Image 1 (cartoon, helix red, strand yellow):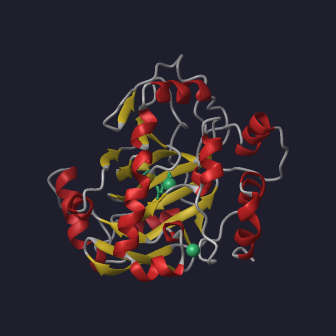
Image 2: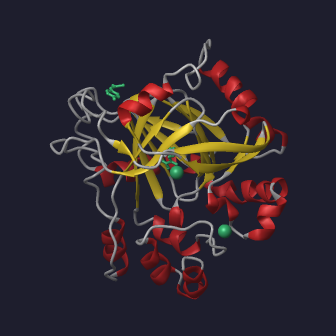
Length: 331
Ligand SMILES: NC(=S)Nc1ccc(F)cc1
Ligand SMILES: O=C(O)CNC(=O)C(=O)O
Ligand code: NI
Ligand SMILES: [Zn+2]
């Protein structure tokens, strides 16, 4: 078996290899990349997402989110407080202000130490889940707005035609902005391109060990666990690498820099933080290997998770027994 230790693998496709997206995902998996839950893909030197990022300041962040923490440094939740709208130019200025800017640091490891020591004592503001794309329409390779849709994948594999669409989202981040431990909706893949700015550090649990993370989360957030059998779907819980190590949870970490893609694989739990002002673009996708994960995906039915329109069809077709209860939490 390839990659038995479930290490995060890094790929350097040639421009020829970068033509066929599906084929290269399949190649990565033939080398065992999915066992880690996360892979890095460095694009060919000849490739670019767009010409410049000089004219993005007028993009609107309609609902910036202030991420307010509760708990202890290594085990905490965050809730999202809605703030007034601001443009990307205004947001960048805020990110670079004395209150919010990245502190002096020696290297990525030093900054990581500072993040886990001090994150809970600050409330950074995130521009998340903004529908849109920064890929040039003439970019033909690995354009996240031009991927085959999940609905067409389900139709190709299972013969059922369903409603729904599948478009990218933009994320504008600043120092300490945080993404909580989660897998994707319906345990789908995700792909994330860091367009511009400071790095993003990722943590990931191998899919074959996801239930170990779930068990620890139930122990560490006992009230949340009683309230919902799938509360990590709420995307609000953080557990530090130190606490994961103390509890013997297998995981890996890696830092993504501007110009690099990350792919998360079905049922690969991940979490992380931004180093400073940046912009990422991400979208979910599927392959034939995903279908069995979609059939088995846990669901939140307590009402907190609240998902896109398009997940309805996924649950309806792949999980018909669960559909009645799930839809109740969504109305
Ligand atoms: N490459 C960068 S950081 N360009 C940029 C970012 C924000 C903005 F408002 C205008 C331009
Ligand atoms: O970048 C972020 O804030 C979160 N991204 C993801 O969880 C992802 O791409 O799957
Ligand atoms: Ni994700
Ligand atoms: Zn729930």
